[PDB]
Amino acid sequence: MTKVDFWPTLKDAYEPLYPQQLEILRQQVVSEGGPTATIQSRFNYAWGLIKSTDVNDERLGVKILTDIYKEAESRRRECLYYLTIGCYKLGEYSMAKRYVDTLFEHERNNKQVGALKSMVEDKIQKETLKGVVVAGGVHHHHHH
């Protein structure tokens, strides 16, 4: 009910949508003509595709958020933030890191950015280096 946060949390992503909620956004997008729909109409269409559990909808929303970014303007902050979240689900942390990096530079408070960037930065750092497949076994040799 707090309609004041201009940027939800990353947990909101773990909140799936019903077939009606997703079809409703399509009525507003298609009713306007579909692609010729306003940007705010397509922007939300990519938001629901990211809350989906399948990766097919996440790769589709990312492409939209990048089209609205190259064609729109001002909506860069919302895109850089949404791209970091939509990208985090595709572990493309290289793209998420570069976009969130530019946003965090803005020097804006909102500890949600410092924390979101922490999932991207902690994952590019904690992944190690050559990426270890986690040693799954037990110490065999033993005598000391």
Image (cartoon, rainbow, N blue to C red):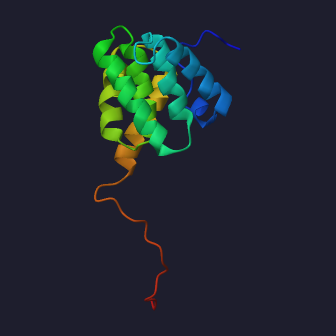
Q: Residue at x 30, y 14 (%)?
A: 71
Q: Position of residue 42 (x, y in %)?
A: 46, 18
Q: Nearer the viewer, residue 41 or 81?
A: 41
Count of numbered tags: 0
Q: Quadrant of residue 38?
A: top left
In this image, 32 relative to 83: left or right? right
Q: Is residue 139 above or below residue 34?
A: below
Q: Is residue 119 visible?
A: no
Q: Residue at x 62, y 21 (%)?
A: 24
Outermost residue toward the bottom in this view: 143
Q: Nearer the viewer, residue 52 or 100?
A: 52
In this image, 107 relative to 113: left or right? left
Q: Is residue 62 above or below residue 139?
A: above
Q: Position of residue 120 (x, y in %)?
A: 40, 38
Q: Quadrant of residue 130?
A: bottom left
Looking at the rendered image, the quarter that the C terminus falls into is bottom left
Q: Residue at x 67, y 13 (%)?
A: 2
Q: Residue at x 58, y 13 (%)?
A: 5
Q: Quadrant of residue 86?
A: top left
In this image, 24 relative to 29: left or right? right
Q: Nearer the viewer, residue 21 or 121?
A: 21
Q: Position of residue 94 (x, y in %)?
A: 30, 39
Looking at the rendered image, the quarter that the N terminus falls into is top right
Q: Is residue 101 visible?
A: yes
Outermost residue toward the right in this view: 1
Q: Position of residue 109 (x, y in %)?
A: 46, 15
